[PDB]
Image (cartoon, rainbow, N blue to C red; front, side, top):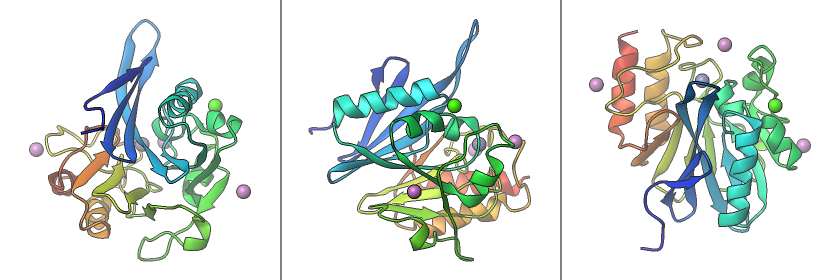
Length: 234
Ligand SMILES: [Ca+2]
Ligand SMILES: [Co+2]
Ligand code: NI
Ligand code: NI
Ligand SMILES: [Zn+2]
């Protein structure tokens, strides 16, 4: 009963505590004269005496505001950040993380695609085994973060993250909730492999009951089945 319930506003950002040491951060794409659209979610994880971040906000200014909220609410240094693909909603704030002295990690393919996508690359590159699990030497001192590359889906480089010791797995933009009308921005998608990649994510974190994703609120495992079924139609 100690966790604050529901959405907490911090300027134009929204924070929601999901577990004793896990929060979801939400930022919107701001368009002058038209307002805010396309909310995007990331994660904040408290791991003992440090904080780990999953994904930036849409911009450097909003990412600096996530860091300000962390300082105010948690007051522990941010040791590292993992970004889940080279799109503006996940990597838009890389400069703000680097200005704060935060070590950044992304799939090697995300770093290679980043300049073509108009993104700043993460400082370090994650590589993966043929079964999709991160090569441990490329993800040093990741604490409870279990990084998995499910195969091409939302993009060819999308990665996912399970939080050890919790019921949470983060599907990023690969997964949409059980009520979603579409899979969202499909311009860079792999329509042939998407369904198998969504199913591979489910199988990599078989015990996770809370599925967190970029463009829907947290849901049950039905979000995985629903996404794979919508991807089967591509
Ligand atoms: Ca920038
Ligand atoms: Co593109
Ligand atoms: Ni380094
Ligand atoms: Ni449906
Ligand atoms: Zn994307």
